[PDB]
Image: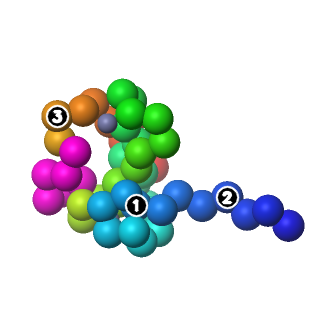
Amino acid sequence: HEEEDVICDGCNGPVVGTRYKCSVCPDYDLCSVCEGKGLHRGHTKLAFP
Ligand SMILES: [Zn+2]
Ligand SMILES: [Zn+2]
């Protein structure tokens, strides 16, 4: 079966918990740590659980 998963573009790891997906770029996501460290911070992101 094809499983769906969100890999953080900052630490190449999985996105567990809050997903911060960029509203500008296509297909860009950050985990809470990379988001909290200011990666990709000038683009608006959708923070959903
Ligand atoms: Zn990360
Ligand atoms: Zn972006």
For mark 3, what is the residue? 42
Magenta span:
35-40
At x 48% / y 62%, what residue is drawn? 7
Q: Earlier in the sequence, mark 1 or mark 3?
A: 1
Image x and y of residue 16, in percent: 45, 65
Q: Quadrant of the N terminus?
A: bottom right
Residue 37's disc number:
none
- The answer as to whether callout 2 falls within 8 Å of ligand 1 is no
Q: How packed is label 3: few (under 14 Cα within 10 Å), some, or many (20 or more)?
A: few
Which of 1 and 17 lies nearest the eye of the viewer? 1
- Above or below 24: residue 37: below
Residue sitting nearer the eye, 15 or 48: 15
Left or right: 27, with 2 as reference point: left
**Residue indicated by mark 2:** 4
Is 45 left or right of 38, judged from the image as shown?
Answer: right
Which SS class for mark 3? Answer: loop
**Number of on-image labels:** 3
| Mark sitting earlier along the chain (3/2) | 2
The residue at which mark 1 appears reads as 8
- Name the spot of residue 24 as percent of width and height, x first: 36, 28
Label 2 – label 1 distance at C-alpha: 13 Å
Residue 39 forms part of the magenta stretch: yes
The amino acid pointed to by label 3 is: Gly
Does the residue tagged 1 have its C-beta within 8 Å of any atom of ligand 1? yes
Q: Is residue 3 above or below residue 25?
A: below
- Disc 1 + disc 3, Cβ < 8 Å: no
Q: CA distance from mark 3 to mark 2?
A: 27 Å
Q: Is residue 33 visible?
A: yes
Number of residues whose C-alpha sits closer than 10 Å to that of mark 2, classed few (under 14), some (14–19) or many (20 or more): few
The amino acid type found where label 2 is placed reads: Glu
